[PDB]
Amino acid sequence: MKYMITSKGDEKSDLLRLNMIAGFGEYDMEYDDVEPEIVISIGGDGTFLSAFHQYEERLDEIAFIGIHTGHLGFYADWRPAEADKLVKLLAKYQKVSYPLLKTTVKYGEATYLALNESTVKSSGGPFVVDVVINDIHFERFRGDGLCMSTPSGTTAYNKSLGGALMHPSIEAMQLTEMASINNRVYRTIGSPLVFPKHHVVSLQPVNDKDFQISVDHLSILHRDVQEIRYEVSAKKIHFARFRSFPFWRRVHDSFIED
Amino acid sequence: MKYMITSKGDEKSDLLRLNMIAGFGEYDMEYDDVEPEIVISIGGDGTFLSAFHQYEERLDEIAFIGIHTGHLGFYADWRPAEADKLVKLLAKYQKVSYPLLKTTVKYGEATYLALNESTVKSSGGPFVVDVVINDIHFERFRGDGLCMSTPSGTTAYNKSLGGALMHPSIEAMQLTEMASINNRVYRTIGSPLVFPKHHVVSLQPVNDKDFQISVDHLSILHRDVQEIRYEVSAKKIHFARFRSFPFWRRVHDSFIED
Amino acid sequence: MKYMITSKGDEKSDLLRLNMIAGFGEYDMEYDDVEPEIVISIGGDGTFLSAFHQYEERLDEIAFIGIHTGHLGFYADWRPAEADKLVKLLAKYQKVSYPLLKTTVKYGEATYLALNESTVKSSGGPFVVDVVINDIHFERFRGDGLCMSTPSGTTAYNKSLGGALMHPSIEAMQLTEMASINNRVYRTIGSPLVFPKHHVVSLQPVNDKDFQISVDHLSILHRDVQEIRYEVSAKKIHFARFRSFPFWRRVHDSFIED
Amino acid sequence: MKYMITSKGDEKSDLLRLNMIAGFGEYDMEYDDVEPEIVISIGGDGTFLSAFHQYEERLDEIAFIGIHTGHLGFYADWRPAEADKLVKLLAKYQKVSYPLLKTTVKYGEATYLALNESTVKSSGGPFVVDVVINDIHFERFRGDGLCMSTPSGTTAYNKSLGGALMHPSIEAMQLTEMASINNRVYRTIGSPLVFPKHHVVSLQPVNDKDFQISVDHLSILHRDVQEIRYEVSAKKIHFARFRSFPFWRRVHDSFIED
Ligand SMILES: Cc1nc2c(N)ncnc2n1CCCl
Ligand SMILES: Cc1nc2c(N)ncnc2n1CCCl
Ligand SMILES: Cc1nc2c(N)ncnc2n1CCCl
Ligand SMILES: Cc1nc2c(N)ncnc2n1CCCl
């Protein structure tokens, strides 16, 4: 069974990576960073984000595993001291799948897959877009930007904006506002919105058509934008589970105490 | 097919009720407020709430219809001028189901069914409870109270507390905080929490065991409480749909403009 | 110079109280709980709140001192181990004054002095009041209640409701909302409001005239209420300062780390 | 008495400007856009913002007047139909002063005067700064940015971020957070902070020293930044008042109804 390991790049992560590779060598494991079936991330949730996007074209044949060399992450939920215990079991577990968010941009198409969220800002000018939900004009948003988050991504940027945390077993997506203007003439919903599967949220410009669109940690500028389309992707990320680590326990350890 | 009609009690609602009853008399409809299969509510969402709780023992044999004599409600989504058009079609539509919230209270059991939400406060003293999620201690809440809302109830009390609006096709429940205390020694999650089906949220006392527990508009005091249990109910409320009125359009008309 | 000491009532506070009284006996200090000029509070901010209200008729002749036997409080900012050091200096310091909030209730008058805040709720029914600012109708509030806080009280209940923290050198008062309803027909400002000196905020009923009015920790029901009047009081509480303990440092220790 | 008039540039504003200039010609008024003593703004609060910054070097000799050709603004509080009535009285009123915010940037100094607010973001990377209040380390902020607002500016960007509205008679400044990160290891105060006169709020970098600093509508990038200093300015903007238009009425008309 093929595998590969990505490292944060610091001294602790590179050394932990070489010790796991040496451990897998004692088994029948084959290192292959081209067509792997097991992808291990050593570092933080940001390193795991990079590992996910390096193989988003083969998500159905890959089970991800995360190791946090710093603090407890949501995707990297393995202690460095438990690395050798992980090498044995990984060489012969069950698979756990999380939903993902699809982002489509159209000009005068480009699709992206997000694990945390996808946000839209205005390249310098004021951000004004009309929010269309299933071909129905819902609101004209006026403010800093908007954030569409996955279930597992609600603990990231979505949380800082006031969004709700939702369990990853729910196939849904959540949209939250960034510093919206609300006076007697400009009105937005304010509340976060949770959309189920097969619901399409479209963002359409009003004046400016240049938007700073981000997907997870990748932020790239798009010029002459006609529409930004959001929907829950049909593809899912697969994790390799070896023990019981509930999502609500991960939330407790990351935010309450540990 | 049996039916019944509840009225808000004012002049406009009582007159609209008698005109619909006379219209149903022209068909083969039988008025029966004991074992009805069609329950019509004329007034507001509060009147619809009363109509739901009067027949929560026969939810699987009843399709609800709401008429708003005041402003546009979420459950009463029919104009009074469309009443006669409603009488004809209702006498020979499709059924639409929404999930519900189950509330269990234990002393030293009482179950309730909520359409909007179920909240917990403290009878006078300070409100302190431990929040347990699937037999896991998540947080010790310290503040005014807590609110567990249904999907269709997220537009009510849940919205005023900062909760997210979620589409009723999602079988889930959402918990939100009321004026929580957060300093260097008392810590809550703050964010709203969305729980899927088969997840159990338990509230357990610390000192005071008397709580002011509410279900929709019913508020009753409970003494010597041992545990408050929350989970998505297996029973669903059934609406009779005659036209396309999306939930996100109901949200737009109630909060954006109409 | 006369003095008195109030205790939380537990073992640690009562013992610390008797040791300070014995220390003051070694000086020319006279214990008098009737007409004191120095009032020491041993326990928490709640105990300090009680000590303030026991002598609100002689605020101009009393300098308050707080000792926290538990965690760091905002009004009780002295460690128990620093008690003997406090007894010496207190027997021959400078005075520091904080503004207070005045609350007037009228029926068919009763004035109260608050150190933290004064809140208004509805005795069971829904809470609806019109908010009048300097004889100008500002908004019709619809929700759980309202909270008018002093500058030093903004770190208490006001903080849990989203209010801003303001330095006690600012003679002002801050009003915050409790779970307000905001749809297309009911509209409140939502933002907290900071009022300067000589500004009068009046609350007037709409239907129900019975309100659960609270002042600091005292909560008492009022029937047949005509108006609730708010303004910054002309009286100030006086603290005895012996060292530099800035307000922003007290906020840091209570909420960031310590 | 010298005067000048700035226009939004559209057809309605330019025509209203030429009609007022012709009206002032019938009096002893002298048009001078170099050393004026009366500055009239015709358009919106953005146009008024431009008019303020064009003459921030002569604030003590200038009384500002605003005219809104669109909707009711906070600084432009005169209807276009009341223009001729304004020309007569302005040619022989009382002066009203509002406080301002001072912003100092230091490299390896540049001072700015803000009427609404001054915000700090990170030029691309993550925004991390230490917040120092009167030479005391208060918090290490981690998020999108920070916003320091004037009293009259609290109805603008400060409001969208959750800040409190404060009456302009209070000489103070208010700081609010933008999408802060708060987990078990990163902690900010969250609440808005209101600082009185003579209090200094300093922002110091951690890693990145390039910041996108904005003052009102001007946004300019600063490289190799050592410190960002905030304090209530000693200079005040002067308005020419002809009638009673309370601040709380301006808030009502802009946000509640009009
Ligand atoms: C990169 C990333 N993702 C998440 C996530 N889902 N929850 C919480 N933190 C996350 N991070 C790191 C930001 Cl501190
Ligand atoms: C009784 C009730 N239920 C709801 C609901 N689900 N959404 C919005 N408003 C509701 N109301 C009436 C309160 Cl105004
Ligand atoms: C009674 C009290 N007053 C305050 C205050 N001003 N700030 C913070 N905490 C306070 N407390 C105790 C509540 Cl934990
Ligand atoms: C430029 C500007 N200043 C303000 C202000 N102080 N309050 C409200 N709106 C303002 N605007 C225009 C933004 Cl819509």
Image: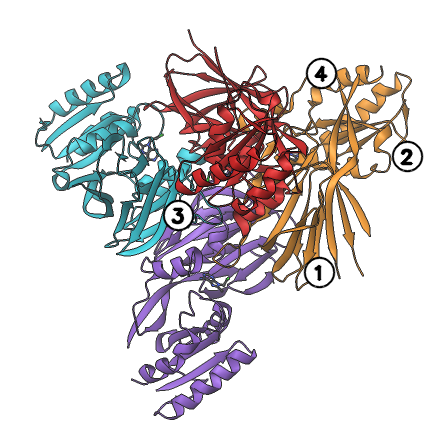
Chain colours: A purple, B cyan, C red, D orange
Q: Chain of mark 2?
A: D
Q: What's the CA distance linking mark 3 and mark 2?
A: 56 Å
Q: Disc 1 or 2, which lies upstream in sequence?
A: 2
- Residue C235 is situated, as x and y percent measured from the top left of the image, at 60, 21
Number of on-image labels: 4
Q: Which residue is mark 2?
A: D34
* Marks 4, 3 in one chain: no
Image: C119 above or below B11: below
Residue D210 is marked as 1
Q: Which residue is mark 4?
A: D243
Q: Nearer the viewer, mark 1 or mark 2?
A: 1
> Tag 3: residue type?
Pro
Q: Residue at x 37, y 14 (%)?
A: C223
* Marks 2, 4 in one chain: yes
Occupied quadrant, residue D88: top right
Q: Nearer the viewer, mark 4 or mark 3?
A: 3
Q: Chain of mark 4?
A: D
User: Where on the image, by quarter, is ligand 2?
Assistant: top left
